[PDB]
Amino acid sequence: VNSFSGYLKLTDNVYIKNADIVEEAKKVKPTVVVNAANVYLKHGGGVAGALNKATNNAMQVESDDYIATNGPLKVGGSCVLSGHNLAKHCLHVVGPNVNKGEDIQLLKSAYENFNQHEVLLAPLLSAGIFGADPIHSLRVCVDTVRTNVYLAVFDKNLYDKLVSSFL
Ligand SMILES: CC[C@@H](CNc1ncnc2nc[nH]c12)NC(=O)CCc1ccccc1
């Protein structure tokens, strides 16, 4: 038994809620919050910009040091950094950005990173500002992640559509 509340069960291991991931993080303080990152860990908008603002830019400062040492992530890749005031850890995961021509098949690789963590609070990768089909992202999540994932979907209208269309 964990501290996530009001989630709808989709599968054995996938749960979903209409919520802002930042507000869920602040309330739950989960072991792992997933950031919808880009390869440069430049946190400007969506999940990344919202989480970073909630850390008072500490996430960006830490990320800039990570990139200066290690160089960019791969599309489909990830790194574990601090969760600051929001979680123990933040798993920065790079889904493909359709608005940049990246291969949607890399979305499965992106979700595979979740399997290294027993429980995660996460957003829908590659959807929203990243330009890919959200029904598809949820399907890839369900078919790829085997650990326990609590999905926070910000847009009410999209949350209703994801639930109603779920197979
Ligand atoms: C489905 C991907 C998520 C990712 N972004 C976030 N997910 C969770 N919490 C967040 N807090 C700040 N951004 C958040 N985008 C949204 O839900 C809203 C954008 C949108 C509007 C209309 C149709 C589809 C998508």
Image (cartoon, rainbow, N blue to C red):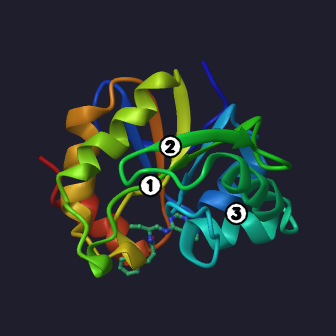
Q: Which of 159/93 is in front? A: 93
Q: Secondary structure at mark 2?
A: strand
- What amino acid is labelled 2 in the image? Ser
Does the beta carbon of the residue at mark 3 sit less than 8 Å from ligand 1? yes
The nearer-to-camera label among 3 and 1 is 1
- The correct choice, above or below, for 138 with respect to 109 in the image is below
Which picture quadrant has residue 94? bottom left
Residue shown at 60% from the left, 18% from the top: 1
Mark 1 / mark 2, whichever is N-terminal: 2
Q: Which residue is mark 2?
A: 78
Q: Establish if 12 lies above or below 38.
A: above
SS at badge 1:
loop
Residue 97 location, quadrant: bottom left
Residue bearing the label numbered 3: 51
Q: Amino acid at mark 1?
A: Val
Up the image or down, 147 lies above or below 105; here it is above
Give percent across and percent down for residue 96. 32, 62
Residue under pointer 1: 94
Q: CA distance from mark 1 to mark 2?
A: 6 Å
Disc nearest the viewer among 2 and 3:
2
Q: Assess disc 1: are there few (<14), some (14-19) or many (≥20) residues with their C-alpha within 10 Å of its C-alpha.
A: many
Cα separation between marks 3 and 1 = 15 Å
Q: Residues within 10 Å of mark 3 (few under 14, many from 20)?
A: many
Closer to the chain start, of discs 2 and 3, is 3
